[PDB]
Image (cartoon, rainbow, N blue to C red; front, side, top):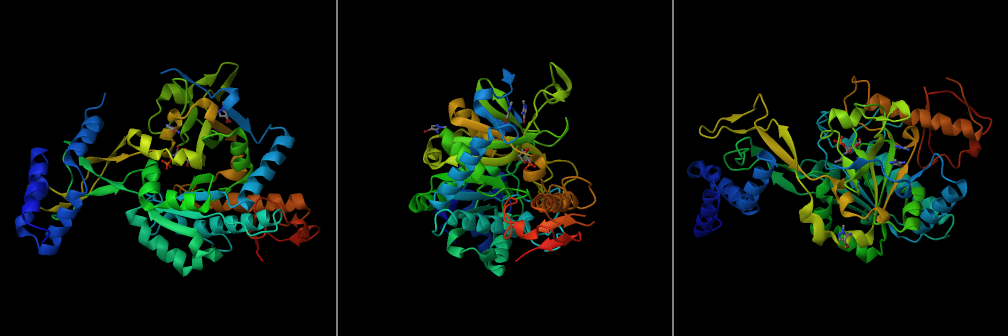
Length: 472
Ligand SMILES: CC(=O)N[C@H]1[C@@H](OP(=O)(O)O)O[C@H](CO)[C@@H](O)[C@@H]1O
Ligand SMILES: Cn1ncc(Br)c1N
Ligand SMILES: Cn1ncc(Br)c1N
Ligand SMILES: Cn1ncc(Br)c1N
């Protein structure tokens, strides 16, 4: 019983807003289930929900590649610059100035796992989860940074989850003792939610006592950094540089020192990585300059014309081919401005099949056709807020840096088999370059042995029979 007169004023607000049907079932509810609905409805402003539904449902460009000033490439940067960025990056780690934010609030709808995507075991000989691989890269990088400071290096690991992934993720991290990181340096927090909206603009009811909600997209990171206390913790620690990435990339160079030292040396607010797009239809965002500003056209939003546009003088090469691999740098100073622009991030509309109560009956039904929409903010929608001179984009090698897990085994791409093959082909490559000989497919190299190919001299001359696993 959370008051009765408060229940009344809340009912007025929703009914005035044309959303009174959320109370249609109140008179047959337990006291617990009533209190659930009251509290959760009180967390949403129904007028604001109408505004969003209206823009989504009744909705109302100069478009060029990024100029050369804002762009760089691992593939053709002066090696003096690559070494200098690497060294400076590593200095910043050794200065305890580098934090990581892992975006891991995804559902993995194409993967159809029961567990968080970061728990998934892609069938490596180690059977290590994506999370563990990433934790060991952090572990290894901390050790590398010690080797040029002679002091302990800490990179705090902020892990952003959704309501659906938060509990299993914390249990997994706990069961694995945080993969050998200090639990005090790993913070698990949660992104926010928005209500799912029917095609007619009506809030959808999951049960007779609960509204259907969904995570607010990876662009919900910003808001969540404030409300979780994470930005505060970063400030306390003296963090100045933050690498943000998606959980699903099994090759991700966590806190990559070249990237950090590149961005810091340019004094950007924001930097981002790309790879050459694989073909016209790859499900990647494209980074470009839109209306004079840095920006991303998401794969779900691009038209055929722009996706298939060819380069004037290279008729089989796409004009727009800087594929977003969700690897971002921010200055800490950028995050200090979140309150000024968080509310300006647009809401992207996705038409979704949302299980709910049929308004009228109460029969909790799984719908056939998309009955409603989910709204999501995207992390990269801050790019057009950022001046070109304070933005930087750097090309990396797909085979070293981007191998996403989108689909279930059996698909044939961006799946557990392509992921394993990419990690094991990278390990063989590194071993062969250090003098090792591989019989033979591929070799898994623990990040604790090598972060990025270093430290493998001990393998010179040794014959390794693939498939193998190099651990301590
Ligand atoms: C909002 C966002 O981060 N979108 C990203 C993200 O797409 P998904 O819809 O999450 O698969 O990962 C892609 C790379 O796997 C990237 O190209 C795209 O732009
Ligand atoms: C010239 N160009 N366009 C996309 C990307 Br990647 C590069 N290098
Ligand atoms: C994108 N933006 N707007 C104000 C400020 Br300070 C920043 N970084
Ligand atoms: C044209 N462009 N976009 C990103 C990057 Br790297 C380059 N060169």
